[PDB]
Length: 56
Image (cartoon, rainbow, N blue to C red; front, side, top):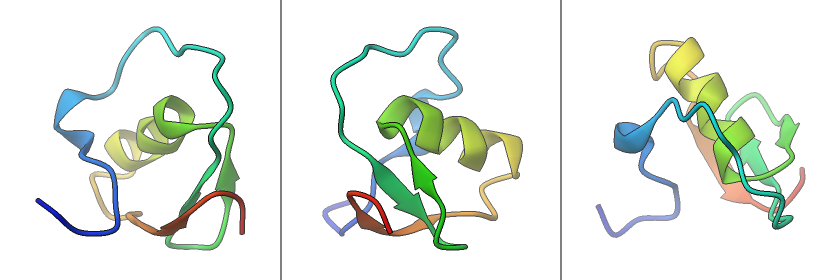
């Protein structure tokens, strides 16, 4: 999995750090960071998927 996206195989996690690193889903939504981003993927049956990192 060496592409431009995060792995949601370790989600959803019931604890997210605070280090800021916003990732944008595929719908063009910003997520505080990797944890809150994937929580969306895992909550959307991996139907969301992001397009790029950072905010939209």
